[PDB]
Amino acid sequence: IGAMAANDPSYGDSLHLKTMPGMVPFAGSDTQRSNAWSRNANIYRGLYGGGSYIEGKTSSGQYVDVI
Amino acid sequence: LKDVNHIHPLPDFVRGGFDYVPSDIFSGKENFEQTLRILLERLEFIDQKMVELAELRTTLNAEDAILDEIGRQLGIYRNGLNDPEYRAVIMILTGNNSKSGTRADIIATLKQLFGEDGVTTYKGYNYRLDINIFNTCMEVTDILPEIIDMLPLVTHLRVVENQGY
Amino acid sequence: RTVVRTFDFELSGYPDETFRVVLDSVTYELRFMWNERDESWFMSLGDIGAQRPTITSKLTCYSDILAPYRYLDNVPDGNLYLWPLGDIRTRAGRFNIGPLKGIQMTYSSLIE
Amino acid sequence: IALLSSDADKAVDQIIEDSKRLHIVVNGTGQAVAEDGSLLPSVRKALIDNLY
Amino acid sequence: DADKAVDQIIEDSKRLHIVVNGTGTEQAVAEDGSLLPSVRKALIDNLY
Amino acid sequence: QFKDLLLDPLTGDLDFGTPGDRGMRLALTNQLSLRQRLYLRFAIWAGDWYFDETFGFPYRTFVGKKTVKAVLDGRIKSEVRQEPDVLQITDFQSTMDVVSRSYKCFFTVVTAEGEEISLAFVGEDEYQYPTPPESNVQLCGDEGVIINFKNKLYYLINFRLPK
């Protein structure tokens, strides 16, 4: 919530790669991440030289910024 | 909050440097990692031995093979002493250089050789002094010559040793 | 051995400072290098334009740096010390060296 | 006097890891790693991979 | 009072010794009263 | 990080502290220092402090005269940015009432927080010099080496038996 609140909805700001303080990286392997992706269960991932969110996909399937 | 002595093995030396792989480009390739790990881990051994080269040269932990070198610089030769007590004599003679042979002072030096309650000292009217030993951990005859040195020029001394009170 | 304070130093904290100073009417060049693992300053002293420094030593508080080196024609005969202005337990740091930063690096010259 | 113990720990710890490996192997679930890096399957796992 | 620790160490060593060398089967007894199996007892499982 | 004597935000006198810890305090956090630096800067009328004729705010220009609200806000908003450690000004609600002829504005200022560079001048030290040994421990060993081994043996005997 801390990453979306102070941001007007009209800008269409995606939540793809934003960094969330407080969260811890997801340690599952590549196969596990692919499984969770099919579930529409987003994961916070420690990226190349950093860590960031992955995708704002809701349970239905549509990207969050659209909603 | 922090130790003043900075000479310590570098914590987690191996994982460092690997942190300098730019963007995980090679990570998970199991061919470059082994080549890098094999080279870096060699420095681990050298890095570790850098400490003992300094740690082990201190008089507290110096082994007899090199403790002789420390004693040689100070003029205290091994003679027939063995390692456990050769360390003691080195400490005793060195400590003598800032002493005055007072009753309180004498107790302090004997304190390092017999624990807290292992020694007591009686005093006499005509220069008589007595030393009592309760918990000796080393043979005393070879240490005796020094025990005379840190006493006034005119002391009259008796030495008695026993186990316990 | 009467001695009088005659010079003070300051460091900007740059890890490879190098500058020229004049002491006892003679001129010398100084180099200061910062050590990461040992968090201490390394000082090198030598003549102007010399190929190699004459003296290299590690800086510490209340220790006579020049003590073992007053037997060379190109080494000052004075006294070089580092002592703190604040709490006595503070040890030399990177940015805390100077007339008011906490540590007073000073040179004093004997009276002749 | 008995401070030879300064050598005992290098064995006491080692037997601790050995007991740990024993426990995981015997009471494991459908593994263990030796100092050589090779794997030892637990009984409840070894019962699966054998020839039937 | 290190004699107290030396005491417990003395019989802990013996318990460990019997456990390691517990013939084919020995049942070492701990201070809690539970029962510890020799190595060769623990090896019945493979012994089939 | 500008240090200075702490001023009580509630009364304006020096913050001598609570009755249980009465004393004197220095402004350490950048927030507290900046608060009083703005308070004094706004409270002293321009030219009224001797030894510095250029310090203060010129209230006499506006008070008692027919003035435009927009001009006043610019000057109010400008004096704030004279401090070198002000990041920005968030909001500004300037309102004026004509019946009572009063003017009252609201706004907030954002400032970061820095490090202490050196603790030499403040209180404590961060090092952990060692402690000399006691009695004949150094020359003959230590008993703790026995106690720790005994405890390890006891805990290992505890581990193996299932519980």
Image (cartoon, coloured by chain):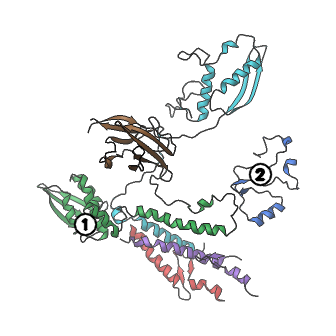
Chain colours: A blue, B green, C brown, D purple, E red, F cyan
Image location (x, y in percent) of residue C77: 31, 42
Q: Is residue B142 visible?
A: yes
For residue C89, which numbered disc appears in the image? none
Quadrant position of residue E25 = bottom right
Q: How many angstroms separate mark 1 from mark 2 (CA)?
A: 72 Å
For label 2, count other residues whose C-alpha is less than 10 Å away and answer few (under 14), some (14-19) or many (20+).
some
Q: Residue at x 70, y 66 (%)?
A: B28
Image location (x, y in percent) of residue F18: 54, 32
Question: Is residue D46 toward the left or the right of residue B86 in the image?
Answer: right
Q: Quarter holding the C terminus of chain B? A: bottom left
Question: Is residue C29 toward the left or the right of residue B134 in the image?
Answer: right
Between B113 and F75, the residue placed more toward the observer is: F75
Between C101 and D20, the residue placed more toward the observer is: C101
Image location (x, y in percent) of residue B8: 48, 59
Give the secondary structure at mark 1.
Answer: loop
From the viewer's perspective, is residue F113 above or below residue E16? above
Question: Is residue B143 toward the left or the right of residue F111 in the image?
Answer: left
Q: Residue at x 48, y 48 (%)?
A: C33
Question: Is residue C93 toward the left or the right of residue F112 in the image?
Answer: left
From the viewer's perspective, is residue B148 above or below residue C51? below
For residue B77, which numbered disc appears in the image? 1
Chain identity of mark 2 = A
Between F86 and F11, the residue placed more toward the observer is: F86
User: Which three-letter amino acid code belongs to the residue tagged 2?
Assistant: Leu
Q: Which residue is mark 2?
A: A17
Chain identity of mark 1 = B
Quadrant position of residue B148 = bottom left
For label 1, count other residues whose C-alpha is less than 10 Å away and answer few (under 14), some (14-19) or many (20+).
some
Give the secondary structure at mark 2.
Answer: loop
